[PDB]
Image (tube, rainbow, N blue to C red; front, top):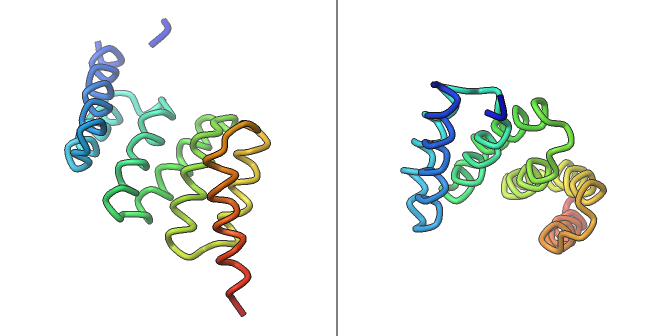
Length: 128
């Protein structure tokens, strides 16, 4: 159906979102992880956990979740955007720019991507 394991997974994801709102990123990571154990075929869980991972400084972990999310759903613009943010935080600005651009070609309006893309391009001119 539109989504039992799939039902419980959404409830855990929802809780995860609630944790994000109060900035309890460790708890958020836990709930998204539980949702993934039940239904790993939902790109949202990975993309959302990547966001929590990034807030916690675990950019490498965020990169891996975004890769999975993008592979599950190639038209998931938010996953490309978060990938850019994580890569950028890992000082991988060339690769970050590539992802921000993809994200923007999918979600053109997004000012968040436009801004962080500029930051990545600016930090990129500093490299040798």
